Length: 167
Image (cartoon, rainbow, N blue to C red; front, top):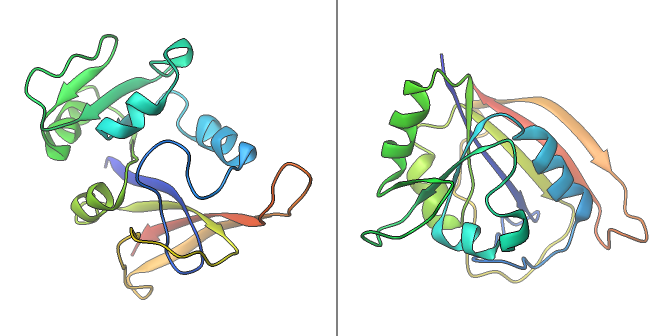
C-alpha cells in the first residue's frame, strides 16, 4: 500500500504557520524534512512553493507537486494539480512507495482523511496561534518513533521528531 504522510512542525498547543517564515526557525527541522522526503513525492501548497528561493526551487531529487485553485498557475519543473486527491492520483501512477504532504491548516484538514502516517515535529513550546494542526484521535494512531532534539545556539526551542501511524 501507498503510505500517505503529512509532515509538519507544531507547538504543544498545535500551532502551525501560514506561509514562509514560521513562528519558529529550526535549521535541523528543515534538514530533517530534506532527509525524510528525499526521493519521494511531495505535495505542497501554493504558499509553500512560492516561499522557496528560486535558487533551490524546485526541490532537488524530488517530484514537486503543487496544489492550487489558480487556473493555469505556472510552475516549471513541477506538476500542478487543482486538488490534493489529484496529486495523490499521480503518485500512485508512478508507483511511489510513500507520498508526503505539506501546507497550512486547510491542507492538513483536507488530507487528514487519507493520512496513514504522521511525521510531527513537536516543538516543546506554546505560542499564540490562529491556524492549527487538525485534531486526530490519539487512540487511532500509534507512535512509531520519537527523537528529542535538544535546544542549542542554533535552536531557540527544543523539539522532537515523532512518527505516528494509523492502526
